[PDB]
Image 1 (cartoon, rainbow over the protein chains, first blue to last red):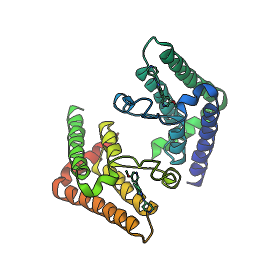
Image 2: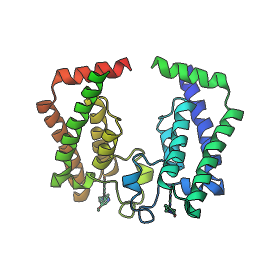
Image 3: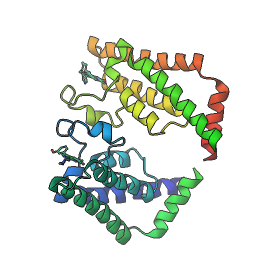
Length: 130
Length: 130
Ligand SMILES: COc1cncc(-c2cnc(NC3CCNCC3)c3[nH]c(=O)c(C)cc23)c1
Ligand SMILES: COc1cncc(-c2cnc(NC3CCNCC3)c3[nH]c(=O)c(C)cc23)c1
């Protein structure tokens, strides 16, 4: 219905705003675009579902997220990929893991403050009816 | 259930085999890998959901296709993207469009010959129950 289309449009507006705020944070530059294969040649083989903030924006615009829960799955994927690909004790690995956890924590904290629980419940109920 | 897992595993085996047969055809080399942005800088902006045969293989392996119908949507996407991005009368554009239609036609013809309709119906009924 028209009311449901308006609901998903509001969701997309909300998710774009959250994603933009993550993307302009200097700490998260490494997660903003797909990896350069020249910098990490084995990334494609080790990480089976790459994800980054530009890809998240494309998915929002393709109407791939019908709930904030589904969006957070991709944010969690950005984090889990980083922990998987950079598990070593070396400072470079530790920096990226810290930034990955910070990205995750920041996204969840924004959502906790700014997402109305009843709005999310509505989205979930519309999704389950499709 | 175990029987349903076996069904989706058989689907994945079937889809990998079809995709491999498309990927080794010389006509379809242009569709085997993501586009090189150096060759087509405006591709990212014009085509909103890029798709290629290596991406299709990754999606099979990530369990993204529960039916042949969903797989054919991505094959159709490879074709529609090509028709959209190369619409001109020039020979280069006409060649790619012809190959795109041939890819689509070939995938459908393989499926028509080799996919049991009752196998596809089972997949669809399992998908709809989830
Ligand atoms: C423009 O700079 C880059 C572009 N693309 C990828 C990276 C990058 C480089 N190194 C990583 N990890 C190494 C750190 C030192 N120990 C070996 C691994 C990276 N790890 C990542 O998770 C991502 C997303 C990029 C990246 C950088
Ligand atoms: C290694 O060669 C390539 C790598 N990546 C992309 C292409 C490519 C080049 N040109 C295209 N179309 C032009 C043909 C002449 N008129 C202007 C457009 C391409 N079109 C496509 O649809 C794809 C997938 C690649 C491609 C080639």
